Each structure stands twice: as C-alpha cells, then as structure tokens.
Amino acid sequence: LADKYASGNSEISGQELRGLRDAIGDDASPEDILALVQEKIKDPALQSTALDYLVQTTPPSQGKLKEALIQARNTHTEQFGRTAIGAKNILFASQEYADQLNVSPSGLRSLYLEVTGDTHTCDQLLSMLQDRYTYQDMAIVSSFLMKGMATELKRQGPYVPSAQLQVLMTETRNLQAVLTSYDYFESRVPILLDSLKAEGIQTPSDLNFVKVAESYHKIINDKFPTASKVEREVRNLIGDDVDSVTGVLNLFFSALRQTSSRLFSSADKRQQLGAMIANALDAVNINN
Ligand SMILES: [Cl-]
Ligand SMILES: [Cl-]
Ligand SMILES: [Cl-]
Ligand SMILES: [Cl-]
Image (cartoon, rainbow, N blue to C red; front, side, top):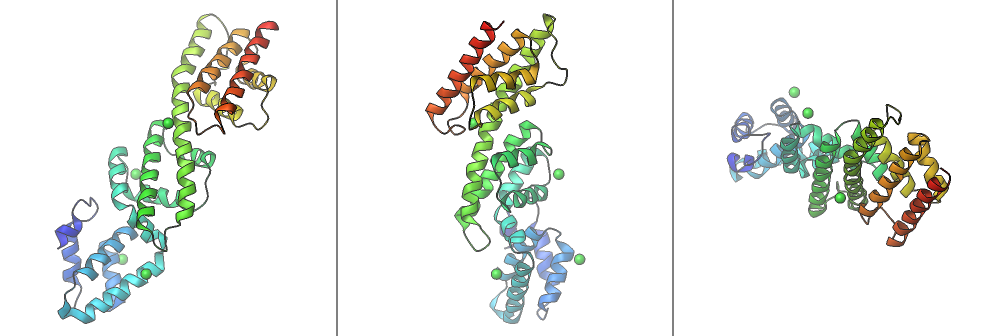
C-alpha cells in the first residue's frame, strides 16, 4: 500500500506514490518510467524509494510493467550508485536529525555522503564542520553521522564501504570527544579572560575559547611535548604576564583531567602530559 510505504517518511506521501503509480501505464518503457519519477520526485534517494514501491506493488497481471520497472530501477541505480543507495539507506535518520536541526533532510544526506566518500580524520571532520555549523549543532551532526553509518553497516551491500565506515566511526567518536573538550574551554576561557581584564591585565582582544582549545589539543597531540614547549605555546597564545600564563596552564591541567580516554594513547601518556604542565607551572613561578 502507498500509505504503508510512505509511513513515517516526511518527504513522500501516500498520495504522491499512488499518483505516480496511476500515471504509469501498463506499456510504459523504462525511460517513460524514469521521466515520470524524475518529474514528480526531486531527490535521488526518494526517487529510489519510489521505484522500490513501484516494483514491489505491481501485481502479477502487469508482468510486462514489473519487468520495465525493474529495468528502470536498475538504470537509476546504475546512474547514481551510492548517491542514491547510501542516501536511501539513511533516509529516516536524515529526517530525524533534520527535524532536530531545523534544516533540510537532503542537505544532511549530502553532507553524509561527503563525509563517507573519503577518509577523514577527526581534524578534517572538525575543519569541514566548524564552518558549516555552530559547536552546539556539530554535536548533533556527529550523532547523525554515527547513526547513519551504523545503519549502513547493518544494511551491507555493494554501495556500503563497510571498512571505511568503521574507521570514520572511530574518527567521529574522536570528534565527539573533542567537542566535549571544547565545551570545557567555552565555559572557562571567558571567565579567565574577564578575570584578568578586571585586574588590568591586558590580553589579546581576539583570543577566544576556540584558539585556547586548539592550543591544548596541539599539546596533547604533539609527539614530543616538553614543559618548555607547553609554556611557549601558552605565551604565544596569551602573552607574557605571569598570571595570564599561570591561568592558562592551570586551565590546561584541569582540561587534561577530564579529556576522554580516547584522545590519549594511554593513561600513562595523560599522566606524562600532566607532569609537564605542572613542571611548566613551577618554572613560571621560579622565573617570575
Ligand atoms: Cl524532469
Ligand atoms: Cl542494482
Ligand atoms: Cl537546510
Ligand atoms: Cl564525550
């Protein structure tokens, strides 16, 4: 039934599916069929969905038509590949998350196909997304990406690059942890900067939580960090006032404690970084 096939799909109605069915004659060619599907349905994922409905609900009396519909669907899949099938696989997730975000489901499916169409590291995902979404919305988008990928791994098929998706899920999980980290900086950085300003300590006026968080992540990802290289990172960020430098170092030490256990290679590595930061705090006081 068209209503059943359209149930819970916010982008196609039962009426639209029945209309398409009724417009397709018994002797329609595959080309005729695709022309009508294209006219009535704009998005390739939804076209593919409509084609599944048409094939599946053509009765035996219309054997010729069923064959033509199967050919039409095969041609559509030949045309689009993963662009149709991958998007179709995540249709309902895209609708759920589009509702959350108040955006188009199709735009989310395009983003999903962009993310899943290449290797991306966490850094690359952050860079793509931060120009397109607020940090708050990035967290929601990350949940969408995770849900979509898990759905495709459940579905399998030639247009699902399962091993690639597994790696992207690891990197997305990493992104989620980075976003949580950024929330700590978003809370604390304005407080620190306002506190310094209230005591007449000048800090660069373009310094914000993102820049501070970027410096912290650079330190935890450095293959050869040292106490001196942490202190220098901080001085490059906020300048040379002893209280400014101390405040950022304490903030980094606190951030370390709370960072996920996926953004370090081991608990030993996290401890080593903490000891470096503590050594930098001591150095800053000695040299004051
Ligand atoms: Cl058209
Ligand atoms: Cl196929
Ligand atoms: Cl949109
Ligand atoms: Cl997290």
